[PDB]
Image 1 (cartoon, rainbow over the protein chains, first blue to last red):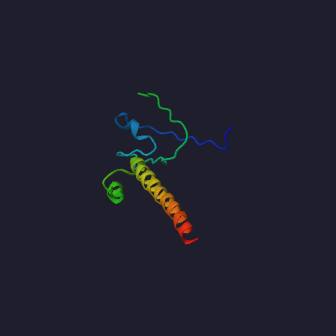
Image 2: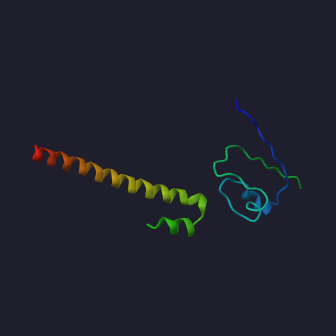
Image 3: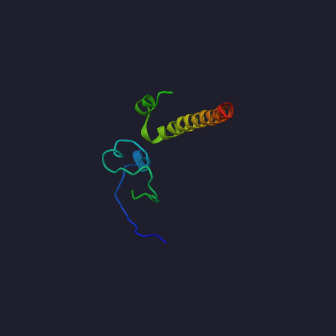
Length: 49
Length: 49
């Protein structure tokens, strides 16, 4: 059982798919979407070419 | 040894490990010093009695 669940969705270039991670740096990690270092959760990505 | 250089010359998310190692070493050394002081104080108390 959890308390609340948040879902965020968008489209990411394949060259920086691994920028989405706690304590991670990159071109868009520091500029478009920042994750907390103690982030608890799951990330899901599938191709939509 | 300088934790300021660790913080500046190296990224935040991974510097936690180095800071933790420094913390453990310094804390253990402090504990050792305190234990030796306790034993010496006991001996001095016997002499004073």
